[PDB]
């Protein structure tokens, strides 16, 4: 496992794509030694703090070692002004923006496929004991319509209430099963085609809401089948929630017959049986 260390001059910004609580993401170009190859790369500049350290390098090397189909790989890092995380550019952008823009041209197959892939990415993370802490549709990027990748895993190891599990809000106990909660919200966002969780509801009223038993509503295009899988991800007991093995297996089984589990309304109406 090898991390690339890039020069400040080897990276050239073009424009801002978006800035979060952690830092800022730049659409940039990367030029390896000489003048032959360029690249379409994304540059994450973290702003405060963390510092060129043995501790930092040790963490960056764990992230550089993360290698999946449905995880974004950390290509390299720059240090000279501040710490900058370098990543291959996903031209389609984040899944959250994608599902809103292509609402009318996304079917049941793709939606169920995204669920399988995100779960698969999370399995890898769980098997390597890396807890993501912040799994959301905005943190899943789009390589191609039928190919999404999870990003920003273990970013708290370097430095989202409505995605967080109740355990994490109160006791800050981040675990693989609290990531399952965030998965349920992530897939809910996908089913609603970019719906804002708990819309019109303040942040400080979320915990008491969840303790009464109230969860996010059944998405219009969901059958009770796929929705009960979601309901399971939001269980009060963390142990009761499904494992990422179970979720992948379930949406895989649903991906075989996709319009049996998601009803998206042609000119003709689609009629569900039970």
Image: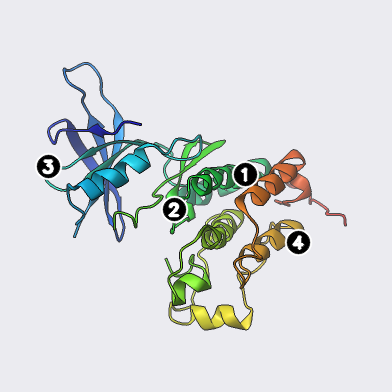
Among numbered discs 1 and 3, the one appearing first in the sequence: 3
Name the residue nearer the viewer: 66 or 80: 66
Residue 224 marker: 4
Residue 55 in the image: state x and y as whole percent: 24, 50
Residue 170 in the image: state x and y as whole percent: 45, 77
Q: How far apart in space, not on screen, are marks 2 and 3 (Cα)?
A: 28 Å
Residue 138 marker: 2
Crowding at dot 2, Cα within 10 Å, few <14 / some 14-19 / many 20+, comes out as some
Callout 1 touching callout 3 (CB < 8 Å): no
Q: How far apart in space, not on screen, are marks 1 and 2 (Cα)?
A: 17 Å
Residue at the spot x=49%, y=53% of the render? Answer: 137
Callout 4 touching callout 1 (CB < 8 Å): no
Q: Is residue 10 left or right of residue 74?
A: left
Residue at the spot x=51%, y=52% of the render? Answer: 100
Tell me the quarter of the picture where residue 112 sits: top right
Q: Which residue is mark 1?
A: 116
Crowding at dot 4, Cα within 10 Å, few <14 / some 14-19 / many 20+, comes out as some
- Element marked by disc 1: helix
Crowding at dot 3, Cα within 10 Å, few <14 / some 14-19 / many 20+, comes out as few
Crowding at dot 1, Cα within 10 Å, few <14 / some 14-19 / many 20+, comes out as many
Q: How far apart in space, not on screen, are marks 1 and 3 (Cα)?
A: 39 Å
Among numbered discs 2 and 3, the one appearing first in the sequence: 3
Q: Is residue 31 left or right of residue 233?
A: left
Among numbered discs 3 and 4, the one appearing first in the sequence: 3
């Amino acid at each position: 496992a090898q991390l690339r260390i890039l020069k400040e001059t080897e990276l050239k910004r073009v424009k801002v794509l978006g800035s979060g609580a952690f830092g800022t993401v730049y659409k940039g170009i990367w030029v390896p030694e000489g003048e032959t190859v360029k690249i379409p790369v994304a540059i994450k500049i973290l702003n405060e703090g963390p510092k060129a350290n043995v501790e930092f390098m040790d963490e960056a090397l764990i992230m550089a070692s993360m290698d999946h189909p449905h995880l974004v790989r950390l290509l390299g890092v720059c240090l000279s002004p501040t710490i900058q995380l370098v990543t291959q550019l996903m031209p389609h952008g984040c899944l959250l923006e994608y599902v809103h823009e292509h609402k009318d041209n996304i079917g049941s197959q793709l939606l169920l496929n995204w669920c399988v892939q995100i779960a698969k990415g999370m399995m890898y993370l769980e098997e390597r004991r890396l807890v993501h802490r912040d799994l959301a549709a905005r943190n899943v990027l789009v390589k191609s319509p039928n190919h999404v990748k999870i990003t920003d895993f273990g970013l708290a190891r370097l430095l989202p209430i409505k995605w967080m599990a109740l355990e994490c809000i109160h006791y800050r106990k981040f675990t693989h099963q609290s990531d399952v909660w965030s998965y349920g919200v992530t897939i809910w966002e996908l089913m609603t085609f970019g719906g804002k969780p708990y819309d019109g509801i303040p942040t400080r009223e979320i915990p008491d809401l969840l303790e009464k038993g109230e969860r996010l509503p059944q998405p219009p295009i969901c059958t009770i089948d796929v929705y009960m899988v979601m309901v399971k991800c939001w269980m009060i007991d963390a142990d009761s929630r499904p494992k990422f093995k179970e979720l992948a297996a379930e949406f895989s089984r649903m991906a075989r017959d996709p319009q049996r589990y998601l009803v998206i309304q042609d000119d003709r109406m689609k009629l569900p049986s039970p």
